[PDB]
Amino acid sequence: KKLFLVFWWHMHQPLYREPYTGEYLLPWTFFHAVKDYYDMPAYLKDFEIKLNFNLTPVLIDQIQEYAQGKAKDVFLEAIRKDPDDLEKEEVEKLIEFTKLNYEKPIYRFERIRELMNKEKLNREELLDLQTLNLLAWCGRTLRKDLKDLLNKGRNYTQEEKEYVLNKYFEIIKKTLSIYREIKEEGKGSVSTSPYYHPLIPILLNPNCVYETTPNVKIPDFAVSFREDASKHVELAKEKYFEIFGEHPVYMWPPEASVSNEALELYYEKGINMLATDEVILKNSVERASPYLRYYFRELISVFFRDKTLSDLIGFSYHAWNAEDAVRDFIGRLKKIHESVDFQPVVFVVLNGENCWEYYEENGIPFLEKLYSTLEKEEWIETLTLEEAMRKEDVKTEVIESVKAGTWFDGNFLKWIGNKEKNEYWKILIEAKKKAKNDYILVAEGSDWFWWQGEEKAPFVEVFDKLFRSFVRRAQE
Ligand SMILES: OC[C@H]1O[C@H](O[C@H]2[C@H](O)[C@@H](O)[C@@H](O[C@H]3[C@H](O)[C@@H](O)[C@@H](O[C@H]4[C@H](O)[C@@H](O)[C@@H](O[C@H]5[C@H](O)[C@@H](O)[C@@H](O[C@H]6[C@H](O)[C@@H](O)[C@@H](O)O[C@@H]6CO)O[C@@H]5CO)O[C@@H]4CO)O[C@@H]3CO)O[C@@H]2CO)[C@H](O)[C@@H](O)[C@@H]1O
């Protein structure tokens, strides 16, 4: 009797490319590409387990633009330049970026503490600030290859900085290839999401928010987003086809968000399986275990992730010693294994790139121990999404209805319902009446609503500039 374990790592960035200037206004796609988007699948080169990935189409677009040398990234330009060429504004940006990241374990360099305690930085000190910001985001592969430069920790030259930059772009250029490789070799399945990671249930029917939060105020949805919901799904199928040669049969619904209408739309667009959150299961069915394969109306297969296990990795284990965390995780799997006489399917689904910067050494000791341990446990069999979808020796159940929600408390309050987030929906509704191009789809991404009305910390103003620029461009 085995326990079936299914990792599904979700990779996404909203579009940071300002539509009028073409400038990438935040470097987050670059930094998570060099740190996580290649290295997370690259673990499969070293560990004989299965790991699955979701790539949003808008993230794929940006990875391609960087790989082709076409991404004009303003923060990266402040890193690349000789410090003598830095604008006062770029020095300010560098210092502000360092301050935002200063307390993260991946920024634990003594030299960074020295630099941030200095009243003024000369050219050598700025070169160190630039290069250490680069190296703080070094991924697992290059932490080995560049170990000597990493251990310097100080006294970097322009040539060394440029060497690191060149190796980083090599990683970006190999990124889509590694996803093709692990897919073709059967080491993992690759899914995608509707194109710009929107909240499909809201686009189809904004009143679905009242299934969980009856008291929420929402704006007057005087325009229909139902066709746009379809377009996000259809365009994602086309992008994922361009990159892999086939249409996707698995999708990750953004924010785990489902509703009866959304599940119908995914079924109508030929999606065979998705996953969502355990809270949605608990809200939809009186008594239901998350270790079964569910069939929604016999139309589409649904797995509900183990929320506890997913949250342990995504939010808890950064605060643990790596050995203890793996012991805890394996011990929890052992209890699931012993708690049923059938073979449970355990979905661990979370963002694949955001938690590691808070782990010691970028989560590498944790993941190397986890994967090394899992590959040796005879009673655990990790599965691709395809294997999980088709496994015969599992328990299944038909469900007829779900209560609309997301993996944030089973509801939509992170994206709608307060004055500021509702203002964004009002802006989008009015812009949709006059829309002329697909930039209206960009503006439908969940990220813009996530940051709005929170507020409040460096760069939220950048997300607001992007959202409003996309809204403006959509009407031309
Ligand atoms: O000043 C605030 C903040 O600033 C910086 O953060 C910046 C960040 O470092 C940078 O990379 C970027 O963030 C990106 C991010 O990298 C992308 O992946 C993307 O994030 C979205 C993600 O793809 C989505 O799946 C979604 O994930 C969220 C959920 O929406 C949340 O509800 C929550 O979900 C969990 C939930 O809490 C739990 O109950 C659990 O059951 O499971 C859920 C999932 O595990 O968290 C996840 C992850 O955040 O939404 C994401 C946001 O839309 O796009 C991001 C940008 O839109 O930009 C950040 C701001 O500049 C700084 O580094 C931070 O340290 C600081 O905290």
Image (cartoon, rainbow, N blue to C red):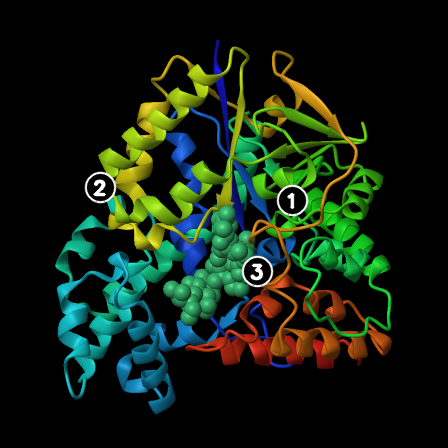
Between 391 and 54, the residue placed more toward the observer is 391
**What element does badge 3 sit on?**
helix
Between 418 and 268, the residue placed more toward the observer is 418
Viewer-side label of 2, 1 = 2
Q: Which residue is mark 2?
A: 321
- How many badges with numbers are in the image? 3
Q: Are marks 1 and 3 in contact (CB under 8 Å)?
A: no
Residue 27: which quarter of the image? bottom left
- Quadrant containing the C terminus in the rendered view: bottom right
Q: Residue at x 55, y 36 (%)?
A: 305
Identify the mark at residue 243; answer none if there is no mark: 1
Q: Residues within 10 Å of mark 2 (few under 14, many from 20)?
A: few
- Residue 411 point in image, percent of width and height: 63, 55
Mark 2, ligand 1, within 8 Å: the answer is no
What's under tag 1, amino acid-wise? Answer: Ile
- Residue 89 point in image, percent of width and height: 38, 88
Viewer-side label of 2, 3 = 2
Identify the mark at residue 152; answer none if there is no mark: none
What's under tag 3, amino acid-wise? Answer: Gln
- Residue 228 point in image, percent of width and height: 81, 60
Which residue is most to the bottom? Answer: 88
Tell which circle, 1 or 3, labels the residue nearer the N-terminal end: 3
Q: Residues within 10 Å of mark 1 (few under 14, many from 20)?
A: some
Q: Are marks 2 and 3 in contact (CB under 8 Å)?
A: no
Q: Which residue is mark 3?
A: 62
How far apart marks 2 and 1 lie (CA) works out to: 39 Å
| In the rendered image, the vertical position of residue 46 relative to residue 17, given as above or below | above
* Residue 56 visible to an observer of this rendering: no
Q: Residue at x 82, y 63 (%)?
A: 225
What's under tag 2, amino acid-wise? Answer: Asn
How far apart marks 1 and 3 lie (CA) works out to: 13 Å
Tell which circle, 2 or 3, labels the residue nearer the N-terminal end: 3
